[PDB]
Image (cartoon, coloured by chain):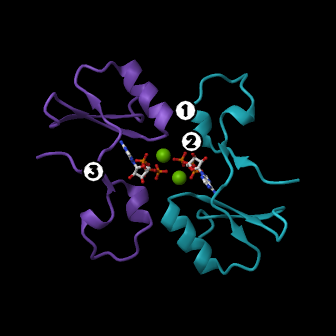
Chain colours: A cyan, B purple
Amino acid sequence: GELVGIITNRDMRFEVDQSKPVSEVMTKAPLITAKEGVSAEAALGLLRRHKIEKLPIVDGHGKLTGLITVKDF
Amino acid sequence: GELVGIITNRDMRFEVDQSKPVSEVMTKAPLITAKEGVSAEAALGLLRRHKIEKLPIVDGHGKLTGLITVKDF
Ligand SMILES: Nc1ncnc2c1ncn2[C@@H]1O[C@H](COP(=O)(O)OP(=O)(O)OP(=O)(O)O)[C@@H](O)[C@H]1O
Ligand SMILES: Nc1ncnc2c1ncn2[C@@H]1O[C@H](COP(=O)(O)OP(=O)(O)OP(=O)(O)O)[C@@H](O)[C@H]1O
Ligand SMILES: [Mg+2]
Ligand SMILES: [Mg+2]
């Protein structure tokens, strides 16, 4: 139940071997994530600073509890 | 005319101050580039390895002489 990475279409596009597992392509942790209760503005600032479109939201124990995208803004 | 970086729409999407110069926003050198005579296959392989959409092509002296994009493929 712990977050160990993320896989997006920029990774999958630049990958040819379809039979590959996710573990060989994904961006492995530590990811750019945020904690519960983060304001929208701070999440937007983090997405702007790190030039990413997805921000996993995790709890106190590292369990994934949400996902914020810049597409929603 | 010596190449000192690249600025793309992701960089300018994540800078709110519209009066900023390029030097403050651009991804600075050394960039992922390639030399003249690189085949489309090696250029595509580099773009796939480094998860970027653009590839400056420079000559033997570091001067920019082309630009290869994944959108063309
Ligand atoms: N939270 C994160 N922390 C670290 N890297 C991340 C995070 N989210 C995404 N990335 C990485 O950022 C890169 C770009 O992925 P992103 O999802 O931002 O673009 P995309 O939706 O694939 O883009 P496009 O719309 O151009 O196809 C990928 O290598 C991805 O693994
Ligand atoms: N050749 C390169 N070397 C290093 N960094 C680069 C290179 N080309 C682009 N970048 C940087 O990589 C990031 C993504 O740029 P890229 O042009 O690949 O995507 P984009 O066209 O802005 O994305 P999107 O289509 O999702 O809006 C930006 O921060 C950009 O400055
Ligand atoms: Mg996009
Ligand atoms: Mg794109």
**Tag 2 and tag 3 share a subunit:** no
Query: Dot 1: within a 10 Å radius of its alpha carbon, few (fewer than 14), some, or many (20 or more) residues?
Result: some
Instruction: From the viewer's perspective, tell me whether residue B57 is left or right of residue A19.
Output: left
Nearest-to-viewer mark from 1 and 3:
3
Question: Residue at coordinates 27% horizontally, 50% vertically from top-left?
Answer: B5
Instruction: From the viewer's perspective, tell me whether residue B23 is left or right of residue B43.
Output: left
Identified by mark 3, the residue type is Gly
Residue lying furthest right: A1
- Element marked by disc 1: loop
Q: Is mark 1 within 8 Å of ligand 1?
A: no
**Tag 2 and tag 1 share a subunit:** yes
Separation (CA) of disc 1 from disc 3:
23 Å
Q: Is residue B22 above or below residue B38?
A: below
Separation (CA) of disc 2 from disc 3:
22 Å
Q: Which residue is mark 3?
A: B5
Q: Is mark 2 within 8 Å of ligand 1?
A: yes
Query: Where residue A14 is drawn, which disc sits there?
Result: 1
Q: Position of residue B6 (x, y in %)?
A: 30, 50
Q: Is mark 3 within 8 Å of ligand 2?
A: yes
Q: Which residue is mark 2?
A: A10
Quick one: quadrant of the C terminus of chain A? bottom right
Nearest-to-viewer mark from 2 and 3:
3
Identified by mark 1, the residue type is Phe
Separation (CA) of disc 2 from disc 1:
6 Å
Query: Dot 2: within a 10 Å radius of its alpha carbon, few (fewer than 14), some, or many (20 or more) residues?
Result: few
Q: Do callouts 2 and 1 mark residues in contact (Cβ within 8 Å)?
A: yes
